[PDB]
Amino acid sequence: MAEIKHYQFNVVMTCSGCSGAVNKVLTKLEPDVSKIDISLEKQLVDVYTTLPYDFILEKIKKTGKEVRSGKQL
Ligand SMILES: [Cu+]
């Protein structure tokens, strides 16, 4: 089992690429993740999933940008 928790991350999404790259990573997590939202303006990324915090932090930064911080909700 897992329940869907709401994670929020701040990733340094300044180039018109990394947004797409994270999104592409999301495309693999889709059949597990419940919901996603992504914001360049406010340099933040909200993901509603089962998968643990650390996994997502890695997954995000993996794409190239740094992950500044995040939290769970
Ligand atoms: Cu970027």
Image: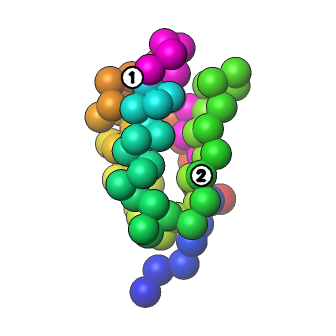
Quadrant of the rendered image containing residue 17: top left
Q: Amino acid at mark 2?
A: Ile
Q: Secondary structure at mark 2?
A: strand
Q: Amino acid at mark 1?
A: Lys
Image coordinates for residue 46, horizontal then vertical, percent: 61, 46
Rounded to the nearest whole Å, what is the CA distance between mark 1 and mark 2?
18 Å
Q: Secondary structure at mark 1?
A: loop
Image coordinates for residue 44, horizontal then vertical, percent: 61, 33
Quadrant of the rendered image containing residue 35: bottom right
Q: Which mark is residue 36?
A: 2
| Position above or below: 65 against 57 | above
Query: Crowding at label 2, few (<14), some or many (≥20) Cα neighbours within 10 Å?
Result: some
Residue at figure coordinates x 61%, y 38% from the top left: 38
| Position above or below: 6 against 1 | above
Residue at figure coordinates x 65%, y 31% from the top left: 39
Look at mark 1 in the image and give the residue it sits on: 65
Question: Magenta residues?
Answer: 7-17
Which badge, 1 or 2, comes first in the chain's sequence? 2
Image coordinates for residue 1, horizontal then vertical, percent: 43, 86
Q: Is mark 1 within 8 Å of ligand 1?
A: yes
Residue 42 located within the stretch drawn in magenta: no
Q: Nearer the viewer, residue 45 or 52?
A: 45
Relative to residue 71, is residue 27 drawn left or right?
left
| Position above or below: 36 against 23 | below
Quadrant where the C terminus is found in the figure: bottom right
Do the CB atoms of the residues marked 1 and 2 lie less than 8 Å apart?
no
